[PDB]
Image (cartoon, rainbow, N blue to C red; front, top):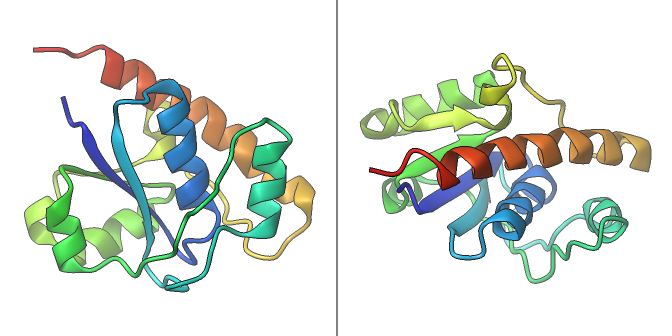
Amino acid sequence: MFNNILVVCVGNICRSPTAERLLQRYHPELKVESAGLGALVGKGADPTAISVAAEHQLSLEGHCARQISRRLCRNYDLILTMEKRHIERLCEMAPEMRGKVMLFGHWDNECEIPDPYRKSRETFAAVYTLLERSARQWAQALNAEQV
C-alpha cells in the first residue's frame, strides 16, 4: 500500500491541491499532500481552483504551496503529477524516485493534462473533470492491488 503520496504541478496552487483533496475524498486514510516544481511557496489554493472545487462541494481549504525539493521527494513513497514533462524533471531531481514518479492520466492511455494557471473558470472545470476521473482511477488502484 503506497499510502504516502505527494502530488506535483508547476505553480502548485491549482492541480496539486485539487488532486490531493480528490484522493482524500475517495480514501480518507491516504496520506496525500501537494507541492510544485516552480511553486509559489506560501500562497494558498487558487480562488478559481477553490471555486470549481466548491461547485463539487470539495474544500481546498488550508492548502499552502511548497517548492518540491529532493528531501520532499524522499519523504513520500509515490510522487504523482499530471504531465510527462514533470515526470522528467522529478526523475532528474531525484533519480532514487525515478521508478515512483507517475501521472494522474496514467490509467487513461498515459494522457497528460493542461495547466489552468490564469485561464477562465471553464478551463479550471475542464482540468477538474479530468482530475476527478483520474483520482477515481488512482483510488481504484489504491483500493485494489493489496498484497
